[PDB]
Amino acid sequence: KVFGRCELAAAMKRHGLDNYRGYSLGNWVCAAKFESNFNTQATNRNTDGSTDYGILQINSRWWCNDGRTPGSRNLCNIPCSALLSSDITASVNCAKKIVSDGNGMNAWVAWRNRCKGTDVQAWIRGCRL
Ligand SMILES: [Au+3]
Ligand SMILES: [Au+3]
Ligand SMILES: [Au+3]
Ligand SMILES: [Au+]
Ligand SMILES: [Cl-]
């Protein structure tokens, strides 16, 4: 599924991500825009053999199982394929564990490099929420 911006904002709020760990909804929308361009099916292989999955590009090195990432963990206790669903529940639930791991949203390098410190409210500007 390719979400619209406000559509994604609304789903993320529905699943409790807005102000989760103090991160406003525009931060989450901005991270999803530069991680996946709002496409739930996005997958990208890392140099190290892990893969990133879904709207928030969650990495098989630590968070999900894809059976081909030797030495990796599965801390969200889910198959990585679940993170490709049109329903973002599994990606949100995992993202809540990631953002609680201690480095907040810096766990998403595209959030640090392209969202952190910017006017992230523009990502929800205009949205009926
Ligand atoms: Au594996
Ligand atoms: Au923090
Ligand atoms: Au905001
Ligand atoms: Au949802
Ligand atoms: Cl959804």
Image (tube, grey):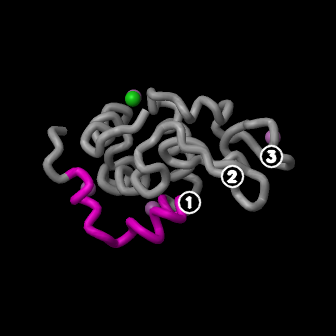
Sort mark 2 into few (<14), some (14-19) or many (20+) by Cα contacts within 10 Å: few
Q: Residue at x 44, y 57 (%)?
A: 34
Residue that numbered label 3 is attached to: 69
Q: CA distance from mark 1 to mark 3?
A: 19 Å
State whether residue 96 appears in this view.
no
Q: Residues within 10 Å of mark 3 (few under 14, many from 20)?
A: some
| Residue 113 falls within the magenta-colored stretch | yes
Write the start and end of the magenta stretch as one range: 105-124
**Is residue 16 found left or right of 121 in the rendered image?**
right
Above or below 44: residue 119: below
Q: Quadrant of residue 102?
A: bottom right
The type of residue carrying mark 3 is Thr
The residue to which callout 1 is attached is 107
Magenta stretch secondary structure, dominant:
helix
User: In front here: 64 or 68?
Assistant: 68
CB under 8 Å between discs 2 and 3: no
Residue marked by disc 2 = 45
For the residue labelled by badge 3, is the local secondary structure a helix, a strand or a loop?
loop
- Report if the beta carbon of the residue with label 3 is closer than 8 angstroms to ligand 1: yes
Residue 1 in the image, given as x and y percentages of width and height: 43, 33
Residue 21 located left or right of residue 63: left
Q: Which mark is first along the chain, 3 or 1?
A: 3
